Image (cartoon, grey):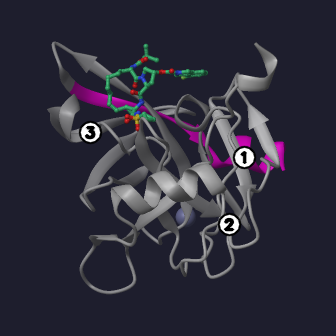
Amino acid sequence: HMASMKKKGSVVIVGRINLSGDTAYAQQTRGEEGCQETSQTGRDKNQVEGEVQIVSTATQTFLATSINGVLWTVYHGAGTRTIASPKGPVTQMYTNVDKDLVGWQAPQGSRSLTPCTCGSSDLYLVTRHADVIPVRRRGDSRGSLLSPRPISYLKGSAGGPLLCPAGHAVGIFRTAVSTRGVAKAVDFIPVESLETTM
Ligand SMILES: CC(C)(C)OC(=O)N[C@H]1CCCCC/C=C\[C@@H]2C[C@@]2(C(=O)NS(=O)(=O)C2CC2)NC(=O)[C@@H]2C[C@@H](OC(=O)n3cc4cccc(F)c4c3)CN2C1=O
Ligand SMILES: [Zn+2]
């Protein structure tokens, strides 16, 4: 029993969504074999850049977003896992299963988004494929897609940001509201809920 019990690996940063220029695009920074090794050791010496990371476990891939010096993502992707870092695995600093939220100290080299104080309801969702999708805010934690899409297009983007027109963080993408496989709306953890957690 006890001597053979395994440990879950760390979450590993495997890429990023580049939002620095005039064109948004995904970049991969680590392949699958390196990901598997890094998840086991928890030691990731790769340089981190940007606000939105593409992250992976052994079994899932999703997004994580830096806001106020914390790299946030969804519990349904990360569970209670550590994140791999240059000095070894780093324990979560926030875990809230009720909000579907986790966070770790933001990695060195990352850039953080600023929480939105605009009160604007014209939002933009950034996906793991670097699609920037307009979303009208419809409540505290809900927004409608201006152009509905099959849920396939959104899968793997939980943990990504909803941004206001000025590029502030408004929320973290959590669930898709789908009818017959088509996403007409999204639900997100509002940035105020992060700010309170902090
Ligand atoms: C709530 C409502 C209205 C009934 O809708 C839905 O339950 N809908 C579904 C539609 C699923 C079809 C794919 C949709 C495409 C993209 C979805 C964004 C996404 C994703 O990309 N994940 S991932 O692939 O990156 C993945 C690798 C990280 N999330 C999901 O699938 C989540 C995961 C699962 O929810 C949860 O486990 N919890 C645990 C929670 C605890 C507290 C609060 C919560 F809300 C919680 C939500 C169901 N999910 C939905 O979205
Ligand atoms: Zn704003």
Q: Quadrant of ligand 2?
A: bottom right
Where, by quadrant of the figure, is residue 42 drawn?
bottom right
Residue under label 3: 145
Q: Which residues are magenta?
A: 183-198
The residue under the point 54% across, 77% down is: 46
Three-letter amino acid code at the position of disc 2: Ser
Task: Say which element carries label 1.
Answer: helix
Task: Say which element carries label 3.
Answer: strand
Q: Is residue 115 above or below residue 144?
A: below
Q: Which mark is nearer the camera, 2 or 3? A: 2
The residue under the point 69% across, 78% down is: 108
Mark 2 vs 1, N-terminal side: 2
Q: Position of residue 71 (x, y in %)?
A: 65, 58
Q: Position of residue 192 (x, y in %)?
A: 71, 46
- From mark 1 to mark 3, how far is it between C-alphas? 23 Å
Classify mark 3: residues with Cα within 10 Å, few (<14), some (14-19) or many (20+).
some
Residue under label 1: 194
Q: Position of residue 114 (x, y in %)?
A: 64, 69
User: Is 171 on the left or on the right of 29, as rendered?
Assistant: right
Q: Is residue 3 above or below residue 94?
A: above
The residue under the point 24% across, 79% down is: 23
- From mark 2 to mark 3, how far is it between C-alphas? 35 Å
Q: Is mark 2 within 8 Å of ligand 1?
A: no
Q: Is residue 77 above or below residue 23?
A: above
The N terminus sits in image quarter: top right
Is there CB contact under 8 Å for labels 2 and 1? no
- From mark 2 to mark 1, how far is it between C-alphas? 23 Å
